[PDB]
């Protein structure tokens, strides 16, 4: 009675997406090649992805290499190509980087981050200024103009039952799973599933580790014992965030929901209280030393097989 009113747009959208993908499939559009290895991390749908967690996990597997993330930076205060971070050191504000590349940079203290709609051009600037040994595309599955040596696709169980935008959340039809070199089957900790394609496949679990402080440093969740917290969220994470806090058994004396565009210009915390919020909110509250986010770690099955795939792209 409403969502079905969106299906006409979905059928149209499918024609457009399929046509573009056919052009790349058949060599009608140029695929550019950077002179160092490129690993893409991506998914098929809008919505919670685990992509951010996986990028952090992957960058850690490559801790022995000079790594640069090539991020889109969809909405920024600056355009073109922008070095957001030089091996952990932020060079711009979130306002200028966009919330996404800035958050990624804060979550990766030894890695460079470059924001550029055109990932190839971002790669060239990085090669010139940062001399990376490997690039990771965060959210790069659809960016077919840039060759990747290892195309990693994250899939959650919900994706397999979903539909193309705007009727559903899929950015591309499920047949495009064929482009993946490796599949990562996500959210196993709450919606476990199997999916056989013949491709190298890795189940991903995320498990609660500890807290992130406002300097984005890891700290024990011990600090929460015998303390009630005030929790808050700067968007619809209201539902999600509240659930996670409950399932973890964290005692929340109060919850506050803010506008999703909130830049926390008017945020006024109380001395002596402890606050919990999301990492996306936390980036706007650095320096408030009584404000924390939850930190989860990726646990991946057959990790050594993934390490082997990664190793082989350096030849």
Image: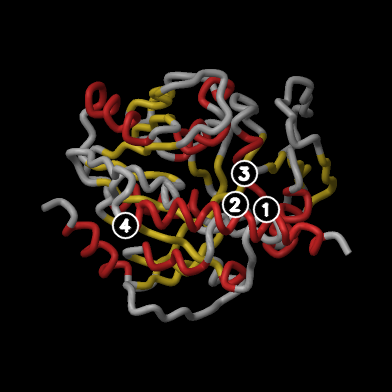
Q: CA distance from mark 2 to mark 4?
A: 56 Å
| Disc marking residue 222 | 2
Say whether residue 237 is left or right of residue 305: right
> Residue 89: x, y in percent?
39, 25
Q: Are marks 2 and 3 in contact (CB under 8 Å)?
A: no
Say whether residue 296 is left or right of residue 163: left
The residue positioned 67% from the left and 53% from the top of the image is 225
Indicate the quadrant where residue 293 lies.
top right
Q: Which residue is mark 3?
A: 293
Circle nearer the viewer, 1 or 4: 4
Q: Residues within 10 Å of mark 4 (few under 14, many from 20)?
A: few
The image shows residue 156, relative to residue 127, as above or below, that is below
Secondary structure beneath dot 3 equals strand
Sequence-wise, the earlier of marks 4 and 3 is: 4
Q: Are marks 1 and 4 in contact (CB under 8 Å)?
A: no
Circle nearer the viewer, 1 or 3: 3
Secondary structure beneath dot 1 equals loop
Say whether residue 225 is left or right of residue 105: right
The residue positioned 33% from the left and 45% from the top of the image is 29
Q: Which residue is mark 4?
A: 26
> Residue 306: x, y in percent?
29, 65
The image shows residue 9, relative to residue 34, as above or below, that is below
| Disc marking residue 225 | 1
Sequence-wise, the earlier of marks 2 and 3 is: 2
> Residue 65: x, y in percent?
22, 42
């Amino acid at each position: 009675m409403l969502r079905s009113s969106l299906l006409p747009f979905s059928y149209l959208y499918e024609k457009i997406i399929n046509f573009r993908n056919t052009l790349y499939d058949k060599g009608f559009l140029k695929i550019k090649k950077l002179p160092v290895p490129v690993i893409s991390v991506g998914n098929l749908s809008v919505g919670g992805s685990g992509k951010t967690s996986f990028v952090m996990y992957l960058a850690d597997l490559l801790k022995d290499k000079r790594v640069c993330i090539l991020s889109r930076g969809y909405k920024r205060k600056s355009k073109g190509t922008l070095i957001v971070s030089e091996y952990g050191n932020l060079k711009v504000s979130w306002e200028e980087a966009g919330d996404e590349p800035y958050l990624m940079a804060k979550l990766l203290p030894h890695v460079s981050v470059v924001a550029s709609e055109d990932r190839y051009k971002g790669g060239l600037l990085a090669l010139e200024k940062l001399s990376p040994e490997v690039f990771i595309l965060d959210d790069g599955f659809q960016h077919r103009k840039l060759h990747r040596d290892l195309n990693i696709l994250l899939l959650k169980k919900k994706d397999l039952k979903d539909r193309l935008l705007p009727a559903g959340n899929l950015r591309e039809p499920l047949k495009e799973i064929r482009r993946a070199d490796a599949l990562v089957l996500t959210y196993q900790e709450v919606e476990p599933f199997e999916f056989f394609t013949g491709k190298p496949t890795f189940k991903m679990f995320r498990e609660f580790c500890c807290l992130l402080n406002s300097d984005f440093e890891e700290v024990p969740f011990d600090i929460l014992k015998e303390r009630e917290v005030i929790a808050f969220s700067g968007l619809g994470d209201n539902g999600q965030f509240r659930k996670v806090l409950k399932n973890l058994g964290i005692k929340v004396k109060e919850f506050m929901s803010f506008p999703d565009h909130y830049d926390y210009s008017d945020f006024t915390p109380e001395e002596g209280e402890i606050y919990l919020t999301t990492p996306k909110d936390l980036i706007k509250l650095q320096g408030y030393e009584n404000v924390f986010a939850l930190n989860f770690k990726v646990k991946l099955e057959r990790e050594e097989k993934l390490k082997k795939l990664i190793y082989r792209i350096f030849y």
